[PDB]
Image (spheres, coloured by chain):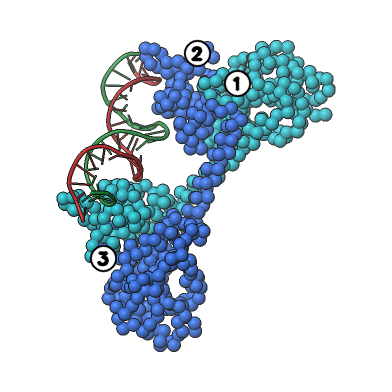
Chain colours: A blue, B cyan, C green, D red
Amino acid sequence: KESYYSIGEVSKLANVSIKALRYYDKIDLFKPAYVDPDTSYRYYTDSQLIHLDLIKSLKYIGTPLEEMKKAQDLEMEELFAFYTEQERQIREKLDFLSALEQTISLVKKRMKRQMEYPALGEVFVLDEEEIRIIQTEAEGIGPENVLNASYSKLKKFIESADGFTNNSYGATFSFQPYTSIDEMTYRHIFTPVLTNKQISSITPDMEITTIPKGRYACIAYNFSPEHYFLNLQKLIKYIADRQLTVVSDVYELIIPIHYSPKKQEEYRVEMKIEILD
Amino acid sequence: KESYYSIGEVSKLANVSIKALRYYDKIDLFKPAYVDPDTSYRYYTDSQLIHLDLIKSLKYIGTPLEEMKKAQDLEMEELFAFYTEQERQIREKLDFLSALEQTISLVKKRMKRQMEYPALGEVFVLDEEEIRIIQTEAEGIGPENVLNASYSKLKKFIESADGFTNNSYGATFSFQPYTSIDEMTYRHIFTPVLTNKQISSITPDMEITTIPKGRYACIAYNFSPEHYFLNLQKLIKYIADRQLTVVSDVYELIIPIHYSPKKQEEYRVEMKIEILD
DNA sequence: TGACCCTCCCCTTAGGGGAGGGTC
DNA sequence: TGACCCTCCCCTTAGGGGAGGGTC
Ligand SMILES: COc1ccc2cc3[n+](cc2c1OC)CCc1cc2c(cc1-3)OCO2
Ligand SMILES: COc1ccc2cc3[n+](cc2c1OC)CCc1cc2c(cc1-3)OCO2
């Protein structure tokens, strides 16, 4: 080859845009063999095309352009290692993505269950699978004064283990024949976990526990301050009428229907309590 | 909560940077409940913190910010679907990454073999594993006039199946007792394939074939115009002396030692030919 | 008085999309 | 004369890093 290739020829031959070529030129990653001193036209030698091989390959695997500059120097000996490195990072993304995929699936699983609920406002008994959770004591907190900010530390944990943040906010309280909401006080407030991934060094003011597998007398409904208590009451009554034996605290889960700052807020509330007979 | 949270409080509570908060404000993704008309200070209500849940989660899975805006509207019903979509894309990246990982491994495999070669300039017989390749006829092309551009269409194929571009350039020619390089003419020029991934609708001027598994009389060495022919000669002589039977064309593979535009170019050349006894 | 917060401005990857103007 | 090529400029994700200046 005693000639030269014009920018467009190289582009058609290497399947690399002219824009890409001008950029690799500016970047001093791949500069033409000769630039016409007048027209400023870019000209390339055939032997030089070989350098685009590495460039295109590294680009395919996401290597940053400036990163390539150092790679084009090493001589097959170290280039080997360079790849072993790239492999490590590739597996990194894979593990992340696999985990992420699993998480999403679980969020959907739980999400579907709330969508296929028997009936709102009515009490019923069903067999539940255990649900793992992270809890901390309520410290006086009760139905009338809980805040989203109250779940801050809990959420920081689930977040650094799941990436995803809890979908539901939970609380518990002694099963009593209350006559008023102000008589109520939460024992614990909790958030369920998704990934059981070893919780990054948990502090002792948190407990990794579970809402055990068993039979539960439940009731779900769309939140309304004047319905919260009356629904608790249905539950209390239902258990008394069938003479059931409660063997856990009442478990309370609040999950938002939407996260739109536009529409009026609405939550799904679910109270369940483990029973025996 | 009859008060407000200052930007920094929300930041500490939601584990979201103040910068991030100001940006989500500008973007109209998450704006404070109230902005002090004088100080311009940003103030947030506790109930509002709940909207950051979706934001943080979608952000964790790579959803673009403007994309989130539409997601915060849908009500759990469609939000479910939205995730099914996200799952599809997640698997997409996974397949890609898995493939990519496999590719890199192969490039390393081949790369290592060239690094652990018996001896340069000397002829020897070894048992080889089959190597799949894509070839096209040489059309007169020979050792003295092959160009990188000659492998253009071939490379466009391997590239759209492997992402990675071939590491070695190949050619073949009839095994003859040549007396001169100018007597030589390639039958085919080829590039080996990495992924056997169904080659995207291959045109008939290309053949998907293979350098079969078998015994080969080989010789590798660092390229030098005056060594190309003399090494071919060693091969021709070696086969004559042991009275071996050649049962293929001579296979020629050229692979660059580096892709640095700084240092002098250097290639690794390997000639092999399948024999019988 | 210190932390706390605000606006403004500059910077970052790898180019794609033109626009205005010469050029094999 | 048309394609081919060049330089210049604007634009793109999600903010982080200050800088200069008021503020619970
Ligand atoms: C976003 O999370 C929320 C959002 C809103 C919530 C609203 C209420 N609770 C938790 C909430 C919660 O818990 C996590 C506790 C039970 C309750 C009783 C009431 C009432 C409001 C509430 O008005 C008077 O009687
Ligand atoms: C980057 O790829 C290259 C680079 C350089 C190459 C150089 C030569 N060949 C292929 C090459 C190739 O093939 C793909 C064919 C054999 C040959 C005989 C010769 C000679 C040069 C070459 O000088 C006189 O005798």
The reply to whether residue A207 is visible in this rendering is yes
Which quadrant holds the C terminus of chain B?
top right
Q: Tell me the amino acid under the disc marked 1.
A: Glu
Q: Which residue is mark 1?
A: B266
The reply to whether residue B188 is visible in this rendering is no
Q: Which residue is mark 2?
A: A3
Which residue occupies the foreground of this view, C9 or A230? C9
Q: Which residue is mark 3?
A: B1
**Does label 2 lie on the same chain as label 1?**
no
Comparing labels 3 and 1, the label whose residue is closer to the camera: 3
**Does label 1 lie on the same chain as label 3?**
yes
Which quadrant holds the N terminus of chain B?
bottom left
What residue appears at the point 53 percent right and 30 percent down from the top-left corner? A71
Element class at badge 1: loop
Comparing labels 3 and 2, the label whose residue is closer to the camera: 3
Q: How dense is the environment of label 2, judged by Cα within 10 Å: few (below 14), some, or many (20 and up)?
A: few
The location of residue A177, given as percent across then percent down, is 36, 84
Give the alpha-carbon distance from disc 3 to disc 2, as whole Å. Answer: 78 Å
Residue B225 position by quadrant: top right
Q: Tell me the amino acid under the disc marked 2.
A: Ser
Left or right placement of residue D13 versus residue A73 in this view: left
The location of residue C13, given as percent across then percent down, is 41, 35
Which residue occupies the foreground of this view, A259 or B5? B5
Which residue occupies the foreground of this view, B160 or A273? A273
Chain bearing tag 1 is: B
What residue appears at the point 58 percent right and 39 percent down from the top-left corner? A84
